[PDB]
Image (tube, coloured by chain):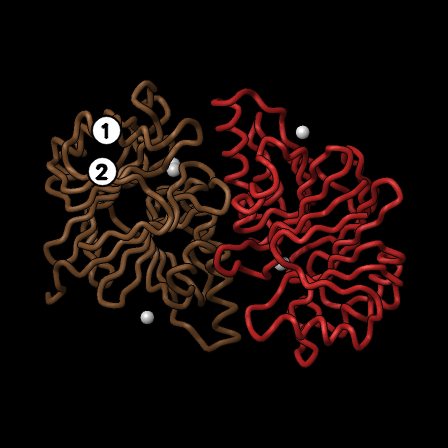
Chain colours: A brown, B red
Amino acid sequence: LYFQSNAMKMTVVGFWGGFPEAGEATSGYLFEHDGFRLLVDCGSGVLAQLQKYITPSDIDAVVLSHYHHDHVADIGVLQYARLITSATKGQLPELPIYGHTFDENGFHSLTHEPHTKGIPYNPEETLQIGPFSISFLKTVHPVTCFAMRITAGNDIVVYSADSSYIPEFIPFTKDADLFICECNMYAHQEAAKAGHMNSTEVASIAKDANVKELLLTHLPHTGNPADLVTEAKQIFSGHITLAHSGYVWNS
Amino acid sequence: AMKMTVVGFWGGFPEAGEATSGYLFEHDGFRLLVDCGSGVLAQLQKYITPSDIDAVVLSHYHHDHVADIGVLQYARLITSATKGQLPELPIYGHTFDENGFHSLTHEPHTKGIPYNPEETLQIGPFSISFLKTVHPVTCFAMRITAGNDIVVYSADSSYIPEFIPFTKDADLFICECNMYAHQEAAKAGHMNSTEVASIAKDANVKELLLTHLPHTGNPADLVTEAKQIFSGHITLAHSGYVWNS
Ligand code: NA
Ligand code: NA
Ligand SMILES: [Zn+2]
Ligand SMILES: [Zn+2]
Ligand SMILES: [Zn+2]
Ligand SMILES: [Zn+2]
């Protein structure tokens, strides 16, 4: 394959855990490589926020970690956007939306023929979506969920999706250039019961896996989330970024 | 007295940084959200908090009118767990879409409450009657009263003459206007500016608010088109538009 390294751009579209704060969005991350636009998760407010960066026609594929509302809320209106745009501005190609099949109802919802098509992913195999190669790790969370290791050439981006701490994250996240990790809890808070991680746990993974940059996301709605960075810095010495709308990372 | 804030107004899907159908009604401190589409929970918090919502009522289960119900359920759950227990939030909807109605319940945070389109519904200080619209899925327009004020919300529909008695003397008619005057609307279960203006005229409404807007052309032309037929006050929906009685 002839996909170039160091030519991937990741833009944070939404980053709030559970529900969005004012004027923003829950989980949604735009990955771009040589004109191919991959949307990772598609939560509440994501279609509105996405259009700060690209049009709905510009999306080439969507991939989903799990079917919680904060990760899929805008799939339906995305399907309507493709249908309406095709009718009024010119026919678009069928949009593939990649999801797991452990929630059959959730997976079925991804297809709105002929505008979008649900395509299953197999978490035990490596998926190719345009220039992106993706492998998966099953997380620990109240519904079936998969973390993703997204590569193009030699680039490595890991997205935790949602999880409580598991040691399997260490080998999975090994040497990642960017680790986009949920951090729903502060250091003083127990997170595992809820299927989430705290800043201590997240920082531990970043350190053990020797990641280059840690991006704290899926943020809580109490406190000052900047404190998560301060807490994580006590443990992990690499670069730490707090997710915000329009944060851009270049590989 | 009654107040209405446009939270979202785009038809089908939202434009950048905005939202699809969602209208916040307020009377005597009671906050009623009419429809709950995409981007609505994000936009709503420019005005009130999720805790502040007292009830929600839904015209139909198309994605552009219900997309944010799930994250609203999560907002109530999360807020109760972290900031203090909230009352159970009633979400009123029709029962003809069984799966859609069932979704509205997430105990103990929200509860689906059926409305009967043949009866008048009482939600706190608001009284709502319904008109079945013509649209690809089952849908109901709403005549919403509090005190001496009347607001009619078309929800989504192709033109039907039953709108005229239903909308009679409304202080505000919030009407979908998905098509320009030159465009066929009925076959899509929508209305054009000519049809909308025809209802406002025949019903003698006091203000007309054009909403559920299209994503082509210049929507200001809808106002110009409607004014050729309806001589009353005409407003094009935008984020944060406030109507007061
Ligand atoms: Na393109
Ligand atoms: Na209140
Ligand atoms: Zn989540
Ligand atoms: Zn989740
Ligand atoms: Zn609609
Ligand atoms: Zn509709």
Q: Is residue B227 left or right of residue B86?
A: right
Q: Are marks 2 and 1 in contact (CB under 8 Å)?
A: yes
Residue in the image at 26% along x and 28% along y: A230
Residue in the image at 60% along x and 74% along y: B218
Residue at mark 2: chain: A
Quarter of the rendering occupied by the N terminus of chain A: bottom left
Residue wearing tag 2:
A240
Q: In terms of secondary structure, where does tag 1 sit?
A: helix
Q: Nearer the viewer, residue A38 or B16?
A: B16
Q: Upstream in the sequence, badge 2 or badge 1?
A: 1
Q: Is residue A210 left or right of residue A111?
A: left
Residue B190 is situated, as x and y percent measured from the top left of the image, at 68, 67
Residue A15 is situated, as x and y percent measured from the top left of the image, at 37, 43
* Residue type highlighted by circle 2: Ile
Q: Nearer the viewer, residue A5 or B58?
A: A5
Q: In terms of secondary structure, where does tag 2 sit?
A: strand
Do marks 2 and 1 both belong to one polypeptide chain? yes
Residue wearing tag 1:
A232
Quarter of the rendering occupied by the C terminus of chain A: bottom left
* Residue type highlighted by circle 1: Ala
Residue in the image at 65% along x and 51% along y: B6
Instruction: State ligand 6's quadrant.
Output: bottom right
Q: In 3D space, how far apart are the residues under numbered discs 2 and 1 (Cα atoms)?
A: 8 Å
Residue at mark 1: chain: A
Residue A77 is situated, as x and y percent measured from the top left of the image, at 50, 56
